[PDB]
Length: 80
Length: 112
Image 1 (cartoon, helix red, strand yellow):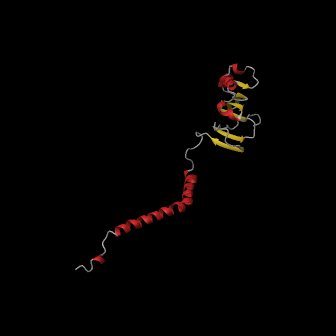
Image 2 (cartoon, chains in turn purple, brown):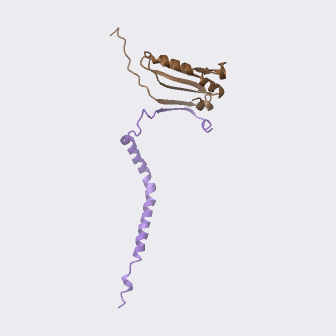
Image 3 (cartoon, chains in turn red, green):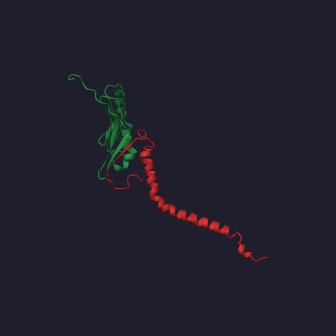
């Protein structure tokens, strides 16, 4: 028994419609998308940064590792 | 104009719910109903017959657990509610066919 012992609640009214009276995916352009954008916007500067930093470190380290495989002509300039 | 009886604009029915919650109240009331046909329709005779089968109850019905109404019996056997009633409220072009019961907070679910 977990329904009926949860919380003391007073004076709240709620209104809901059957699913058959309403649309499944309403106002995609007037409400949905705007909010999607809103949600993306509010988070991008928190998430993106470290991932971007990760990428850099990755690129550096990958290129630096290949550069060290190449040869330095300065080791053969007096090998005649 | 004066002796013409005006026809009212039809009222649209909506499957939906309204929940007014006040845990401070001692017992809960619940009413459920579908759209009825309206005065003129003959089916109302059958609906009323139907409501008679389910009928009604209240904690002072002496018949108790032997009442013919199954819902009434269960109500007694399982202490499902303080009372319940069926109804077929009619109107010109529509109506409400349903039931209402009064139960303790912890027996609402089984009653329904």
